[PDB]
Image (cartoon, rainbow, N blue to C red):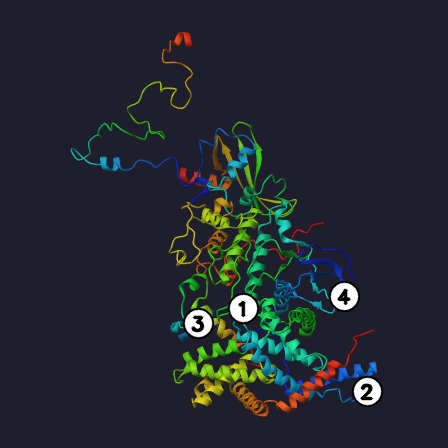
Amino acid sequence: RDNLLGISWVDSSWIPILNSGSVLDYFSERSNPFYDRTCNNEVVKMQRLTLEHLNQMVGIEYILLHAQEPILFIIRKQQRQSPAQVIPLADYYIIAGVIYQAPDLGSVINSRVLTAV
Amino acid sequence: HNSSQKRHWTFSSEEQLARLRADANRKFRCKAVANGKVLPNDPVFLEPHEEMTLCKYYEKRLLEFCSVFKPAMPRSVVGTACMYFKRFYLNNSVMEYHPRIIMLTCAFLACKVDEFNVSSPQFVGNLRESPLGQEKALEQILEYELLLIQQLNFHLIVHNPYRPFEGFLIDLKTRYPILENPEILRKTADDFLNRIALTDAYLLYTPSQIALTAILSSASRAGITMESYLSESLMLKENRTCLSQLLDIMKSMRNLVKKYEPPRSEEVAVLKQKLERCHSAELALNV
Amino acid sequence: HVPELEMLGRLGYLNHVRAASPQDLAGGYTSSLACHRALQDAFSGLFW
Amino acid sequence: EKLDFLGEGQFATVYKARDKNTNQIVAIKKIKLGHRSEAKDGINRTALREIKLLQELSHPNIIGLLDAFGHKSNISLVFDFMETDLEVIIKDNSLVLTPSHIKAYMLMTLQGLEYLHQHWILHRDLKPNNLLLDENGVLKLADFGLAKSFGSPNRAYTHQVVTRWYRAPELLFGARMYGVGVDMWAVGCILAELLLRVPFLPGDSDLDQLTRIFETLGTPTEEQWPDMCSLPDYVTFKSFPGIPLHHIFSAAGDDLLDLIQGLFLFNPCARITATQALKMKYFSNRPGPTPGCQLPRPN
Amino acid sequence: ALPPPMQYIKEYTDENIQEGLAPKPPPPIKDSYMMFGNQFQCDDLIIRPLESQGIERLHPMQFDHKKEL
């Protein structure tokens, strides 16, 4: 919880069972530090075959953005004020069943320059 | 009562209650005059004060009926039954309805409201009557119960002085150790509450005031001084003025108790015969 | 107004006419609750 | 005037009929009674409790008897019209996630409970069923017949009145006395059921609910509830490890989970009071409870 | 969850930070139950466990593998 950018979480048993909706499910788990046990994404784990929960009423949600079938599966965290209104919060990208948080442009540049100086 | 919902129903002055009884008797007399069955100012017609005297004898009889009730009887149920009968009689003329049948209906409703839930056959068993008559009486109770609910205006809840009196006695012991024999004071206060129940003062004042009056009567009876309790009462909303108003109510309450007297048996017997004559005459309902 | 918890001599006294019953206590009838119930009804009204 | 039949019930029949007094359509409840029985109690005992309590309590979160008619043999009760029952909406698959609407329902229930508890009235049974939502969306307790007043002097107390699906452990153990905490336990079951959208604990009666309560929260320790063994009706179930609230219902609100744990505490004194729940952090949070203007409305 | 790619070097290495003669010696051949990986992998076992454990046997003790196969 010190720095979410500097944490990686995985589960080798989950890695064989992985592709598309599977990714949403893995993220949905719970123990992943990025996933919140509060917000709305917890209640989609409670709901069944939901197909539009992010629109009519709103809240913090996690949705797949871009997907490559074998490994690459990018997830985006949105905060909706109303249907047809989306506010992007952050992006968590999964490479080879390893979840990282997408580094900011300015934050990454500045920290690495500090390491170089 | 902080909960209220009965404050509008309670009448501040005894004179207001007497006028309401008079108008209800007059309304029945006017309906009979409209029918033309009986002339106005008929000898059969019963004066409201005479009807009130008959009710007071019946109120004493109702206390005797509650004492001889076959199941154990809650004190709150006894108070509720008396309160229901007086308010129903305030609403409608005493001559139109026999008091004993109405009192049985009030007692059955009082058990249901207080959750005593005495069985209707068990209540019939306590009454002594022919079995066919008991079944007819049970049917009468149901018809009267519907009328009583309309008279209640859907306000079954009643405020009873006994529960505040228990709280006041506990408060008195903790606030001051000066008072002695508190349990004997509680017994005398309960006896005073029973006298107030016979009087119309229960309708006139809120239950908490009646309970406080009973504690004050017990203190005077034992010679204990409540001046220290009066000073803590003075330290409350309205300051000294609130305490002075309470003292004025206590003095008026003593006057009501002294004015009230047990009804003469000979006059009650004449009233009972007149009530039977009113029942012998047939209203015939409405055509 | 009377508080649910007396936080006073009445709470310290912890005394009731029925005193304390273990079976009754587990279900309810806390001594403070019983004292508060009597006091609230006693303090009801008392003003015009 | 009868305009529509709101619902059919054996105890009483609900009609969506405009009042003769008021042109606007209003909810009307008419008692159903049988004169066939040789011995009768006249007005139904549960109906008698419901009418007096409704008249006594005037609150936005409590339904009130605006007018009633006793002139007819049937008794007609006038109440504010309610668009739909809460239970049917919850059992229906939600179109979207509504966690702030769930927070609003609980906040209204606690405020209504606090008002009746302040009046000293006790509600014996609280459940999603027998709960009505108006077009306004304000939550009101439709039935006060289940509710029974409690007093400091010892008196007969109803037992098993609470629903088998949502029953307090003390009621299952047949405790002689009942407390405000029993209502809080029922609210906790409703809150857990609301998140699931299905009843949190299945109750088939005969202590089946008690076995389920033991399975979900583990076996209660003697320290957790005093003299549980001493109570005359006591049953010892298998020592289940128990399920963490965030596993039975996936939800684990930073403050909501703590509130659910307090409601599910076996001891009534330990159980969070309605007043504490009003001051609870979960209700006072950045997510804002729905006023009911945006509450989902059928048709 | 909370666990990382396993706890890092600890215990035996702390012991090992000594000099000349101070470190503990090697452990004895625990000829019993151990826990390599996740399986118990206890000692004293055969190579081909009899099919009698876990399943029915449709073949008699003559077992002339070539004929029965």
SS class, disc 1 = loop
Badge 4 and badge 3 both on one subunit: no
SS class, disc 2 = loop
SS class, disc 3 = loop
The residue under the point 52% across, 67% down is D150
Q: Name the residue beneath numbered marker 1.
A: D120
Nearest to the eye among marks 3 and 1: give it. Answer: 1
Nearest to the eye among marks 2 and 1: give it. Answer: 2
Q: Name the residue beneath numbered marker 4.
A: D22
Badge 2 and badge 4 both on one subunit: no
The residue under the point 74% across, 69% down is D71
SS class, disc 4 = loop
Badge 1 and badge 4 both on one subunit: yes
The residue under the point 60% across, 72% down is B110
- Using the image as rendered, state which of residue C44 and residue B79 is in the foreground: B79
Residue type at the position of mark 3: Glu
B239 lies left or right of D298: left
D217 lies left or right of B10: left
> Residue E55, located in which quarter of the rendered image?
top left
Q: Position of residue B269 (x, y in %)?
A: 65, 88
Q: Name the residue beneath numbered marker 2.
A: B39
Q: Is residue D264 above or below residue A89?
A: below
Residue type at the position of mark 4: Thr
Q: Name the residue beneath numbered marker 3.
A: C6
